[PDB]
Amino acid sequence: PANLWDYDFLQSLGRHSSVTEEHVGLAEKLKGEVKSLITGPMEPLAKLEFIDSVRRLGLKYQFETEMKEALANISKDGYDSWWVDNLRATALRFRLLRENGIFVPQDVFERFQNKETGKFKNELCEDVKGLLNLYEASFLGWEGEDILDEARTFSTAQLKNVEGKISSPNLAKIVHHALDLPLHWRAIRYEARWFIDIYEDEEDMNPTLLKYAKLDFNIVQSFHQAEIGRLARWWVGTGLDKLPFARNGLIQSYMYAIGMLFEPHLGEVREMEAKVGALITTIDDVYDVYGTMEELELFTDITERWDINRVDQLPRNIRMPLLTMFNTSNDIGYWALKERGFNGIPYTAKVWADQLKSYTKEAKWFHEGHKPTLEEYLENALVSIGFPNLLVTSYLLTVDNPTKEKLDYVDSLPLFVRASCILCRIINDLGTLKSIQCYMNETGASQEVAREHIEGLVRMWWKRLNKCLFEPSPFTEPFLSFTINVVRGSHFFYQAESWTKNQGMSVLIHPITL
């Protein structure tokens, strides 16, 4: 029986599947037909809505070139009367163009403002799809784009007020889902599973796209199940499943990794990221449990020196996580040597050393009654959250022509990656001494005021990421998406056990009925 907490079940995954070669040949056929629909003749707003649907169904990885081509064709040609003075069209166009690297100025929304008060016009307050498109579009903004901040607050207020009054149950579901999290902040694979059901009930539903979305979801899922089986057998082989740390650490870590990257061709990378995540949770718990004890000083020193010669001084429940961290980091660095020509061990060793040092510092503060400022706290806590480790590892494993200089640069945590790491930390803190209490102690602010200031920090760092994606960068495709998608993973998982089990069951275990 399916049991996400049962390592016998998890080690069994991948041996048998609903692959059904017929399904594979059928999906290639339907994929060609969907390609034709994306490039073919269509009304312009309807074409934007079709492309947005393909994205929301988790299928953008299959149609990158067609979507970019159709969007360039839209963004260039002639007439604009198909969206000018149409809030719904204007906002969907702004969002999709900006999502695909085509700049659109915020001034495109000025005609919807009162021209004297900066406030959006009251006659839009019941335009449900226009409000919804304006809401989703506002999250593609940059710092200093004040119209889009006003658009966010206005559209949120009005969607909240209109939510209970929407006649279409499906449109009401879409509005409620958006108010929980905008599409820009949602993890791709989890959103795809939700939106397949939603799309089936849309009035503009294209049955070929729906059938392809279901087939492709099931095929990708079979890949994920084989990965889970391998990872479960690894984990049980470490013995860390029997130690009193990180209760569901392996499968939770794999669910987070699925947030970071889901595509089948990144399987090996995803498995390694899952390994690191599992170890991160376990060792986080280790440093929590032994918080003051000198055992942790030896743990940290062994890791800083990357030298296990003194490891038998540690008790077994600490020695086993340490040696599994050591051996796995050596395996991952060796994979880089074997596959990419570059020994990654010095980098996996370093990010782990940094990580434990971050834990040590947090512990120090807690033990000495220290109250750090917000910036101080965050400078340590963007490391302790674990994403410098996970992201630097993903770069090592995917960058082309890896060199010491590229790895040193990413490991320095420049703006783009730093912003992702800070975001993950702040989102974790909002969902759980941390960001809110630190800001309180720094300014005396209310808990409500402090939470609002931290939510504003989330919005601000997202604006910085948005702008980074338009600006020259040493970073290339896989990693750019990794850096955004770990944040999306954080939003989705830090929004009880029933919910997590439900997400894992519906996304990883149960195929979609065809």
Image (tube, grey):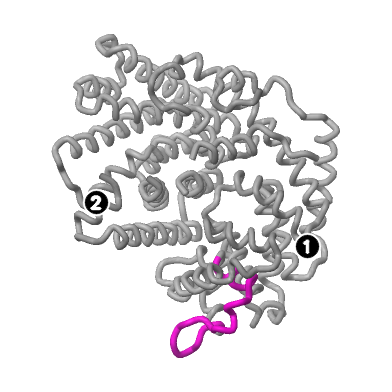
Q: Position of residue 308 (x, y in %)?
A: 31, 14
Q: Pointer 2 and pointer 1: residues touching (CB < 8 Å)?
A: no
Q: Is residue 53 left or right of residue 245?
A: right
Q: Is residue 337 left or right of residue 45?
A: left
Q: Within the image, what quadrant is residue 299 found in?
A: top left
Q: Is residue 335 left or right of residue 171?
A: left
Q: Residue at x 64, y 58 (%)?
A: 173
Q: Is residue 93 at least partly visible in the picture?
A: no
Q: Which residues are magenta?
A: 112-135
Dot 2 falls on a residue whose secondary structure is: helix
Q: Residue at x 55, y 29 (%)?
A: 271
Name the residue carrying label 2: 438
Q: Residue at x 27, y 20 (%)?
A: 302
Dot 1 falls on a residue whose secondary structure is: loop
Name the residue carrying label 1: 204
Furthest toward the left, the residue is 368
Amino acid under label 2?
Cys
Residue 34's place in the image compared with 318, above or below, is below
Q: Is residue 75 magenta?
A: no
Residue 143's place in the image compared with 306, above or below, is below
Q: Is residue 394 at least partly visible in the picture?
A: yes
C-alpha separation, residue under disc 2 versus residue under disc 1: 49 Å
Q: Position of residue 277 (x, y in %)?
A: 45, 31
Q: Is residue 249 left or right of residue 446?
A: right
